[PDB]
Image (cartoon, rainbow over all chains, first blue to last red; front, side, top):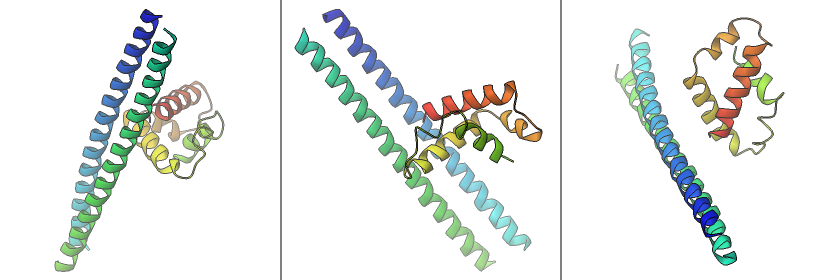
Length: 52
Length: 52
Length: 71
């Protein structure tokens, strides 16, 4: 019971930590991609405004 | 053994729910920051278009 | 041309049954659509012709299960 409880607690803590790290990396990559897409959209809107 | 297994399962479920809620709050904050940055870039592009 | 790939997977297999709420449509649609569309550029090639074969079931099942389960 102590080995199964320690293994389940360690596996749940490692899975929750890996899921939290993957969610933080995915949120940071999504925020950086959203910032790059916003900068590219602002540059394209400025170039289209200058051409118009 | 029963109290340790029940406390380990409840602590693992509460840690997983808290980590998922923290990941959802971090994703919502990153989406709000990306929306604010996109709105600021759109306002700067509109001001640059009006100045042009 | 992404209406057949997104409409023939969530409304056929069972990816839209797990997120039937109105508040989960923006996070699930944006996270699953941006993660699945950004992590695999070959799936868009499936929209270049017909489909309904091994690439539609494999790409729709893997992209819908990985994108819907990894969000």
